[PDB]
Length: 212
Image (cartoon, rainbow, N blue to C red; front, side, top):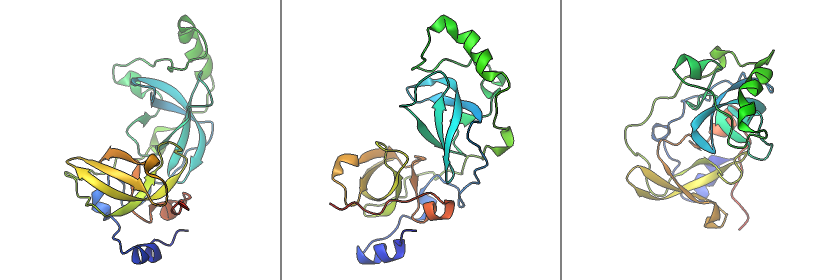
């Protein structure tokens, strides 16, 4: 459990206030179980919705993998993400499920495929999907502030970070003790940033600053 209060005091810093983030005041409960199927936006083509399977769970996050694709392109979504839904959601809304971009068969094999994987499949019930957190209506971050952030190159990891710079609705996230190579800009609404303490409150491991 990372001693944020010690760290803030030794670096002379403020943590960014909770009202800055689009995250629930309390981490949402994660009732998902590994093997459950659900519907998610294909990160490699965000216009497609695809069947995904929970392959890991960590704090309030799911590690998802799209059925019929590959094991090298897993992605993580919070249980209260608006990019995952219960199965049947897409269709109820006038949509069609799509094969993943990395689908391992040929396309005409897709309709048959959906049937086989949906047959007696373990499916996440709709009630375990958490509601979308209220959002701030402007950027309240400020240069200097510290926070917890997913490292988009190794997303299993959430790490101690700092806001470096601001241009309107974008913040620039830096990772303390790492070479600015893991830095990124993101919208203040991003679901990949959290107030200091969030990880401990949700049982997600939280990386201390790097050793550089």
